[PDB]
Length: 363
Image 1 (tube, helix red, strand yellow):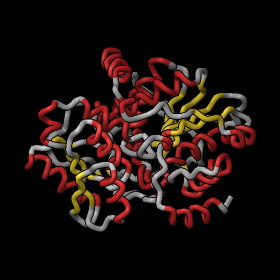
Image 2: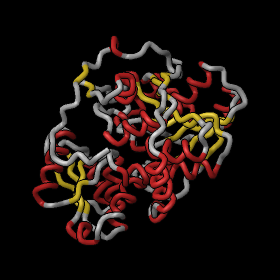
Image 3: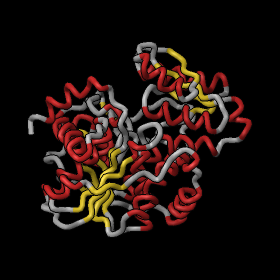
């Protein structure tokens, strides 16, 4: 696309109501017919992804064979463990890549974003490595322990607003006012290329993949991974996964244009996105095979699945793609194929397991 700099959003509003969802069961593929994208643009992405300095902050995370899930489903079920990054999610990658491309002058001024979660941690970490002040704007109502999490990384946290939107608005206007570069959570080529490095790793770690399942909030992660994969392993399906109650990418792809959901279920907070990105929606139209929807009980059961493997806890958004991959395997009776799901993060309040156990128990 082109960069959207100053105009307010005018994306067509859609009332988020059960009657609008495609009538599919969990794991049933909502088909996308990819348009292909541009050869030169994709090539530029490939090279930028390969040149990305993410390893200044990130590791090549494990691609782990999930034994129990594999035995149950009769496939080779692999989980890409981005929850094993320093900040417990993949988001250090995009943030560092984009920030590392800023001029030394821009970095000396300092950067700004609004977040009290996974993106905030990635940005703060990148700020520390790049020796620059990152101002993270959070609502005044933010649990002290998350403020400390970001301050621990060296973030200059600022309290403002009662919701993420007011904090965000304030961070954005404070951006134009103070002349600070805004670091976007997903809607940016630099960020997309950072997340794309996960495609490189997965492909390096495993060939002959039937499908890679990827959680979709804003669409940065999937756009990045799909960009690498559709050039390097074109026969592999790239499938996005979303909660029924937050199906903004699915609805957008179905309508043929971005769509703004009136409200979203927040159980999977990281993917509770009302409006997908401009760059990322275009990449999905161009590249991905389709979308799969999951419910909160399926998400919760996936958290239990991973616990049952090694007693690690994923956050709800981090388990979304696992739920999607598993459901897809059962729906299509996939057998003896390689399946990858991305475990995208593990920053969840301990107390949320109260609700998760309740939903996981439904079987």
